[PDB]
Image (cartoon, helix red, strand yellow):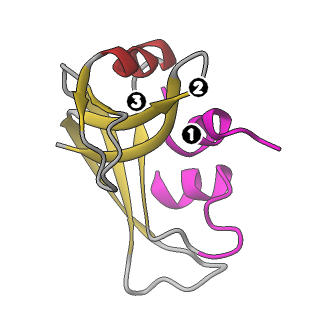
Amino acid sequence: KETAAAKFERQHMDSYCNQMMKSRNLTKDRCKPVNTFVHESLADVQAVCSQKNVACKNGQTNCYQSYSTMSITDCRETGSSKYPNCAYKTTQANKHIIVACEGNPYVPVHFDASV
């Protein structure tokens, strides 16, 4: 088993899109429709677990929003996309991230949104 934290790191850490989505194995069983990569240090992202507590989209209370904006990339599939040619539009932005944190140590296990 990978672990949710490791999966989080695989899917969302990258201190473009077709290639990274391929590299991280997000085009494997299918083309994952959308995914965000974060271009900050792992430590900066992990510290988010002690920042602004906010509700998760699913209604759980263990989500956290970064006090600072962070450099991210949104990968969002194109219409012309078909596996194994999964095709993605890349969109850069600087936004606050919201992640769900769990476990001991208390670390990100889910990317919820950016604002």
Residue 65 sits above or below residue 114 on the image: above
In screen coordinates, is 50 left or right of 25? left
Distance from disc 3 to disc 2, alpha carbons, whole Å, reads 23 Å
Is 20 within the magenta? Answer: yes
Magenta range? 1-30
Task: Kindly report which numbered mark, 3 or 1, lies closer to the viewer in this rendering.
Answer: 1
Helix, strand or loop at label 1? It is helix
Is 25 within the magenta? Answer: yes
The residue type indicated by label 1 comes to Phe
Residue for badge 1: 8
Give the number of the disc on residue 103.
2
**Which percent across, then down, holds residue 57?**
29, 54
Count of numbered labels shown in the rendering: 3
**Which percent across, then down, holds residue 93?**
22, 42
Asked if marks 3 and 1 touch (Cβ < 8 Å), the reply is: no
Give residue 37's quadrant in the image: top left
Viewer can see residue 14: no
The residue type indicated by label 3 comes to His
Residue for badge 3: 39
Distance from disc 3 to disc 1, alpha carbons, whole Å, reads 14 Å
Pointer 3 or 2: first along the chain = 3
Residue at the image point whose x is 56% and y is 50% from the top: 20
Query: How would you rate the neighbour count of disc 2 (Cα within 10 Å): few for under 14, some for 14-19, many for 20 or more?
Result: few
**Which percent across, then down, holds residue 69?**
19, 27
Helix, strand or loop at label 2? It is loop
